[PDB]
Length: 71
Length: 168
Ligand SMILES: [Mg+2]
Figure 1 (tube, rainbow over the protein chains, first blue to last red):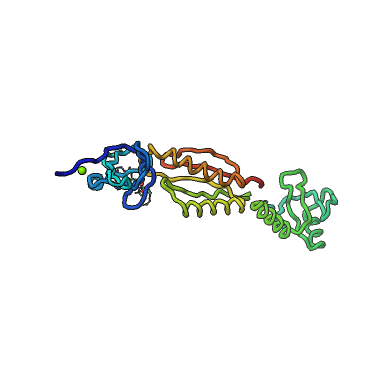
Figure 2: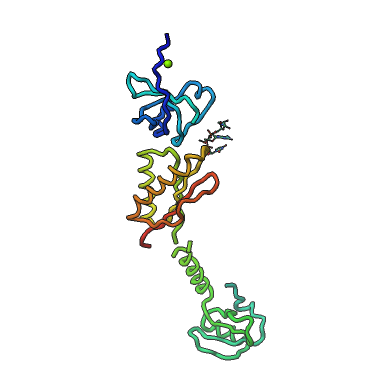
């Protein structure tokens, strides 16, 4: 199956937390603890509070996303 | 500073000034020496370049000591406060920030002028903004204590500010 309902929305990076879990003030609205993708981890790509990153957000509970695009 | 006293006066005729400001006129060297011996004071060469050299009867060591004292005292009320530098950061956070602020306050109280610097790394797109903002916030916090001197400035990989205490 692989049930695709994933919202591909952009957002400005807000708060740098541990584990590379970035609060991202989205273009959708409210900021959530959206963490970094595995791809990014592999390629060694540093995000700072001041970038417009794409966060792939879930419809079940908008509390956790995923930073996919580099800045 | 350095004067040629007693027997370092090779000069044949010397114009002699007494212990208090009494001008004893144009005298022989030997006579001057004798006079000095009589007072149990030194015969100092305070005017080596003047006609019949201006030679003073004084306690030379004491004078030297006084001079030294003067030099020393001057260099406290001329060294007279310095620059303390605090080096903040980008994603800087709560408790630490507060501590830094406290430190700054203490420095201001002491009397020492504050370089409010931030050392940077890379990704200089975000850098100017937040860095500037933090500095401004700090200034606002201490507008009850310090005057803004050097407003936001890049030094290459650095961003520096400067504050001075209000009433000095
Ligand atoms: Mg999916």
